[PDB]
Image: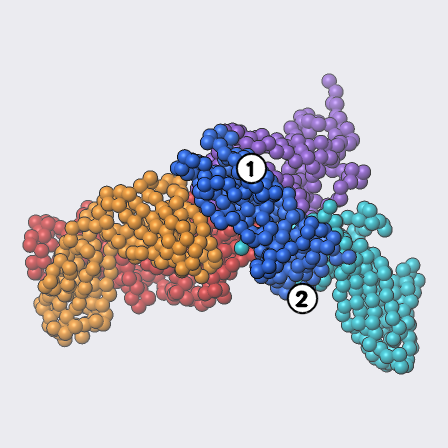
Chain colours: A orange, B cyan, C red, D purple, E blue
């Protein structure tokens, strides 16, 4: 199979900026090279076909170039609607392959996360389970590292993290991390800490609480 | 002028069995003929190894090479009567009589070691309910599309075998003169 | 006028098999090639196989070869994809894709169909356990405060989390569900000015249509 | 009009039904032409371009007769020309060149077998003139080398058709 | 009588470029001819889609379909002189002169939109050191084994193009009348 590599995997750019993404094939192909655009819960859409043809309903700002092994898709002026994932595909020789795709996100000023730690619920405790939730909201870039410390000790087990997509309005990111323990093991420890390091700060932000 | 003749062939063995019944008894068999036996499937764009769209089999020559020695005793004789309508005598091991004796198309084949051949014209099976077919005509011989695998059987021959106390073995070749039309070659690039 | 409609979302148990359909409209399938593509969640697109509705010739990706079978019914102008011996790995969205109708069309945008979700789970419908999340009494942010609700152990997705039945749809962040122990868990946070709470009461409304259950939780 | 700089080809096909060619008659005579029988002697297929002589980016195609309903798949931009090595290929230049093919049709009797006559006027079989269930005649497969401009063709199809058994109905008054 | 004739073909486009030099200048090119271009590889036991062992190309007809409009100005003219020995004029973009003007095989081709064709006989390349070849003889035309991929180039034509300030584009068809021998079909069973 012909391997398609797209680079970069993830890219950020401010509006009005020109953007170029590339797709390289392990072996040469013809006008059987196409690009697809995909938005979050929508199906992939044929953006550019035959390496440089527009496809119906595609804005002028988009162009594609290349031949041989190397191809690229360019956006003269990036707009918000442009934020999506772009996949190059090669219909030249089966099995037909797709590139990893390049996720294009909107760049914005850096912003620190606003952390919030939440203790378990009484109702939840009655069931014999306890979950401590930590919210890290509205921050940029997406890169963030959260750690949980129970009595100063790192706790990796039972942690489930989830991130939202870049906010439509503010273009920020949000994350939630949940540590789930039993009523017993939870009752045994005094302090629970949600620690997060972000580019925004050298000093890791901490939010903690003690039982009652 | 895409017309083309060639001569096509196949061969297989057959066994008549040793028998115990002292009265003369007969083994009935039949012969259907499909060209899918005769063809290898081609590859790539050309699905069939022979580049034509059309075919019509002019003649069928059916040969009979015994494995039976000349030194073999208990010698017999059979009949060879051409069937062209798919209505067959039922295939039987030991028939009390010979059903093939009073056809117009009966040729006589001696047993066990005697060489035989029939040089004749096929008929396919167009519709099983009607079983309708041409007279002997080269000029208005209709054409058949060369297909992948759904090719028609040609009802060719019913055969008889007087049974013996020894096995009778026959390398039975079938040879066909087949006419062709519409060379249909595909050449993908590179 | 060209359109490819796919069968509805499917939930099936592991070990089972299913048959997906893609019915083309506005064009004849005989005229082109039909393809099925699979995309795992948060994963990339993977081409499964293609068929020529005219001949029935089919091509497959080796990895898919035992597992999937592609067939097509020109009469019905439909293409099918059958998956056998389902596993969780199979869960993903399946797209069927084709083209125009010859005569030099090699274009007409694309028709990767709407896609069909396939979820493979042994789990039974389970209503969500909703737990309110209230602050420990610490100044999280100078004035303002953030509340949350935890929706745990429900199946299948989705669930709807509204605050104050909709009165509060600002500063809300509902995080995508994550599977834990074959059940889904999700959390939604809400930010409001320190002025309003605890003054006004805030409730989060969760609804799980599969279970036909709606819960309301007030935060103290 | 196309964008691919390598030479590419547009495949199309041509089936032929007489129901296109006929108006339905009224009253007792269901078909406007009073016959029971028909057999199409010849088919002449004409090609009038809307394409100017002044048009650049000039091309060339092929014209190879299909008579068995087994068609090259209709494609927009084929890497090659599949019609180049048929026995029935005639050459058509592009964009503005006039073309015609003066030939004999073949209908589609059975799709599984696809069986048909040789070139014979004398034993040309007859076909019942029907209302609407009339057979397609598989006539022609065509190729089009693709260009950066649109090529437009007023394509006439002309048939010499033989007839039999005039079947007129005259209700009274 | 395994002798067989057919007519074989290929076509491809070519671009002569727009130029800036005001003096008349010439673009030299050459034309070699391999049948591996013309053939698709067969599958299964038959490696080549065409069942023959032997071939000899009787004629080569090389066609010239311009994309160039009749409305195009800056009109030119070229030469068409047949090369049959692999000794070529060096392929050049803008030659000061026309090297093809005083060959015996020169035919004149006008530019940009003029139709051209050459209806002639090929010569392969037997040994590059010697470059030896037949006279014009159908009867003692030698035979060539149909091979898989190692088929010989046929040195056919050297061409000239007077350069212009516009691009000149030509759909160049090459057609060959090729004679054949020794049909070699393989039919594996089932």
- Measure the alpha-carbon separation of dots 1 and 2: 52 Å
Q: Position of residue D3 (x, y in %)?
A: 44, 42
On the image, which quarter does residue D171 sit in?
top right
Q: Which chain carries label 2?
A: E
Residue positioned most to the top: D173
Q: Which of marks 1 and 2 is in front?
A: 1
Which residue is rendered at x = 63% and y = 47% of the image? E60
Secondary structure at badge 1 equals strand
Q: Which mark is residue C200?
A: none
Please tell me which residue lies in front, B28 or A12: A12
Q: Are marks 1 and 2 on the same chain?
A: yes
Residue under pointer 2: E188
On screen, residue B187 above or below B98: above
C112 and D168: which is toward the camera: C112
Location of the N terminus of chain A by quadrant is bottom left
Q: Earlier in the sequence, mark 1 or mark 2?
A: 1
Residue to which mark 1 is pinned? E109
Q: Is mark 2 on a helix, strand or loop?
A: loop
């Amino acid at each position: 199979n012909i391997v398609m590599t797209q680079s970069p995997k993830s890219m950020s750019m401010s509006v009005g900026e020109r953007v170029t993404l590339s797709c390289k094939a392990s072996e040469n192909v013809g006008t059987f090279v196409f690009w697809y655009q995909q938005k979050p819960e929508q199906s992939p859409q044929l953006l550019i076909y035959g390496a440089s043809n527009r496809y119906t309903g595609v804005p002028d700002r988009f162009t594609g170039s290349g031949s041989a092994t190397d191809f690229t898709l360019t956006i003269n002026n990036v707009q918000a609607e442009d934020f999506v994932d772009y996949y190059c595909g090669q219909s030249y020789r089966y099995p037909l392959t797709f590139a990893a795709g390049t996720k294009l996100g909107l760049k914005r000023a850096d912003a620190a996360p606003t952390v919030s730690i939440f203790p378990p619920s009484s109702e939840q405790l009655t069931s014999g389970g306890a979950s401590v939730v930590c919210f890290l909201n509205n921050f940029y870039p997406k890169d963030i590292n959260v750690k949980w410390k129970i009595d100063g000790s790192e706790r990796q087990n039972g942690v489930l993290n989830s991130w939202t997509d870049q906010d439509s309005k503010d273009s920020t990111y949000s994350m939630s991390s949940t540590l789930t323990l039993t009523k017993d093991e939870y009752e045994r420890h005094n302090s629970y800490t949600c620690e997060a390091t972000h580019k925004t700060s050298t000093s890791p932000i901490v939010k903690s609480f003690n039982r009652n | 002028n895409g017309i083309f003749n060639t001569r096509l062939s196949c061969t297989f063995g057959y066994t008549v069995k040793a028998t115990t019944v002292r009265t003369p008894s007969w083994a009935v068999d039949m012969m259907r003929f499909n060209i899918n036996d005769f063809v290898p499937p081609g590859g790539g764009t050309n699905k069939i190894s022979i580049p034509f769209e059309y075919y019509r089999i002019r003649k069928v020559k059916v040969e009979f090479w015994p494995c039976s020695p000349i030194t073999q005793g208990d010698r017999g004789v059979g009949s060879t009567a051409v069937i062209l309508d798919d209505n067959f005598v039922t295939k039987a091991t030991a028939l009390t009589y010979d059903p093939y004796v009073n056809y117009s198309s009966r040729h006589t084949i001696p047993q066990p070691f005697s060489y035989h051949s029939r040089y004749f014209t096929p008929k396919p099976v167009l519709d099983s309910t009607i079983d309708y077919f041409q007279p002997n005509n080269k000029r208005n011989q209709l054409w058949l599309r060369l297909q992948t695998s759904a090719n028609v059987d040609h009802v060719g021959l019913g055969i008889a075998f007087e049974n013996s106390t020894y096995d009778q073995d026959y390398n039975i070749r079938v040879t066909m003169y087949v006419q062709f039309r519409e060379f249909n070659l595909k050449d993908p690039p590179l | 006028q060209v359109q490819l409609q796919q069968s509805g979302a499917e939930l099936v148990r592991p070990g089972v098999s299913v048959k997906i359909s893609c019915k083309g409209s506005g064009y004849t399938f005989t005229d082109y090639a039909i393809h099925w593509v699979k995309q795992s969640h948060a994963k990339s697109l993977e081409w499964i196989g293609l068929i020529s509705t005219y001949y029935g010739d089919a091509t497959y990706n080796q990895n898919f070869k035992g597992e999937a079978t592609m067939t097509v019914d020109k009469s019905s102008s439909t293409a099918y994809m059958e998956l056998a011996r389902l596993t969780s790995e199979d869960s993903a969205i399946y797209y069927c894709a084709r083209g125009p109708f010859s005569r030099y069309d090699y274009f007409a945008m694309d028709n990767w169909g709407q896609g069909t979700s396939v979820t493979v789970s042994s789990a039974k419908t389970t209503p969500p356990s909703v737990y309110p999340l209230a602050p420990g009494s610490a100044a999280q942010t100078n004035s303002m405060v953030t509340l949350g609700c935890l929706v745990k152990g429900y199946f299948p997705e989705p669930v709807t989390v509204t605050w104050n039945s909709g009165s509060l749809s600002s500063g809300v962040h509902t995080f995508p569900a994550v599977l834990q122990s074959d059940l889904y868990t999700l959390s939604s946070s809400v930010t409001v000015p320190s002025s309003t709470w605890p003054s006004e009461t805030v409730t989060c409304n969760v609804a799980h249509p599969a279970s036909s259950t709606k819960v309301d939780k007030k935060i103290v």
